[PDB]
Image: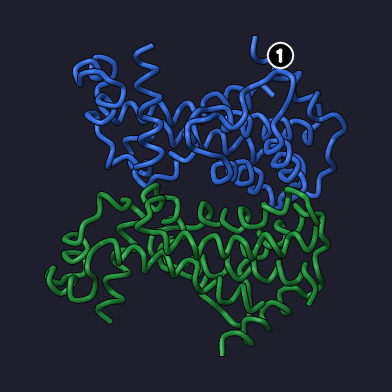
Chain colours: A green, B blue
Amino acid sequence: NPREEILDASAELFTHQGFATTSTHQIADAVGIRQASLYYHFPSKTEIFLTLLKSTVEPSTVLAEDLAGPEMRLWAIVASEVRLLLSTKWNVGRLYQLPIVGSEEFAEYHSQREALTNIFRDLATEIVGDDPRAELPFHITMSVIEMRRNDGKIPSPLSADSLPETAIMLADASLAVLGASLPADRVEKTLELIKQADA
Amino acid sequence: NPREEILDASAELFTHQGFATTSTHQIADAVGIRQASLYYHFPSKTEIFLTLLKSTVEPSTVLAEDLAGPEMRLWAIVASEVRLLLSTKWNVGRLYQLPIVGSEEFAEYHSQREALTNIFRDLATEIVGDDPRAELPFHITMSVIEMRRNDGKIPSPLSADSLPETAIMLADASLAVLGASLPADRVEKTLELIKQADA
């Protein structure tokens, strides 16, 4: 739809140029519409950017919340998040790195992000107790942002039948750093949760 | 010195606002000098930002190059880099995340960064062979950028007598993800290299 075209164009521009340098004019001239048609869908560039930020975290929060012992739970959650970040045309995961998202304009995003971070931390604490390594799984998950392409081709299309290698490797590492043992058939077990949730 | 004041002011501004939004006027009005005095030291904002980027990586490359078996070498290198990133007033490590540093203007930085990345990867390959986990230590090292403060107080002053906890934890994790065994007295062994190098 037209809205989706604006979002796709904006994800390309924001991920390559940053926020400040990108304008509603460029986004509209890139979608091939007049500026008024952009404004019919979005009050400004700020709302567009917020929408993209949410897409990065709200799905994982919803799923991460809904997700067996703690090793399997954490592994599945890491794999799913990394799976989500590899599933998109552009690398919209790098958007949280922009210093502007520090501003209170984006407080909605802050809240959602710390809620997701909390989910990772509390799961890891179930595994290693009062150990500062509990912080690490989230950060390991987010390293996918510096791994994938941003040329417009999707790194790994979402599939019900597989997990991409990078999601597997990063979820394995998320448990490794905690000294936790990696569960048998973890890929199949994870895939089941995704079928469960996504209906 | 005046140059150092400009760099400090610019590191504060770039790390909080990004590149595009920061101007030579703001930097000068923040240092409390006229704009002409800024221009005496730097042709533009771009050179200032490059200088800061280099500081993030050239010291580690020099040291990382100059750095026992592979576990100890990698551990020391990770700890030193994380040590360097925790040693500065502002979080200048987040500057490479700005999409603008993708531009060829900053090709000098690209080269230096891939050279540092190569050093981490080749060390890790000495440990795990042809295993994609070799990619992970660098990324684990760089997670410190999302851990530390950026309010102007230095997270951990450089000391000859200790390593901060976060550097220890991240260097431990860099080996953990590779299944490698963590060497005894690694903190003291690392500190020795730093005394050696830094004379």
Q: Which residue sits at x=64%, y=87%? A: A196
Count all numbered tags in the image, as a single digit: 1
Left or right: where does residue B63 sit relative to residue B101? right
Q: Which residue is mark 1?
A: B196
Q: Quadrant of residue A46?
A: bottom left
Residue A57 in percent (x, y) is at 50, 67
In the picture as drawn, the residue positioned furthest to the bottom comes out as A199
Secondary structure at numbered mark 1:
helix
Q: Which amino acid type is marked by label 1?
A: Gln
- For this rendering, which residue is in front, A128 or A151? A128
Report the front residue among A119 and A165.
A119
> With respect to residue B34, does A183 lie above or below?
below
Mark 1 — on which chain does it sit?
B
Which residue is outermost to the top?
A: B199
What residue is at 40 percent from the left and 63 percent from the top?
A90
Task: Tell me the quarter of the picture where residue B145 sits.
Answer: top right
Residue sitting at x 28%, y 82% = A1
Instruction: Tell me the quarter of the image containing the N terminus of chain B.
Output: top left
Q: Locate residue A193, reporting x and y percent.
A: 66, 82
Residue B196 lies left or right of residue A90; in this view the side is right
Instruction: Give the left or right position of residue B182, taking residue A139 as reference.
Output: right
| The C terminus of chain B, quarter of image | top right
Residue B193 lies, with reference to residue A138, above or below; the image says: above
Q: Alpha-carbon neighbours of circle 1 within 10 Å: few (<14), some, or many (≥20)? A: few
Residue A174 x %, y %? 70, 58
- Tell me which residue sits at (30%, 31%) in the image: B46
Image spot of residue A51 (x, y percent): 36, 69
Left or right: residue B124 versus residue B101 is: right
As drawn, the residue found furthest toward the right would be: B184
The image shows residue B165, relative to residue A93, as above or below, that is above
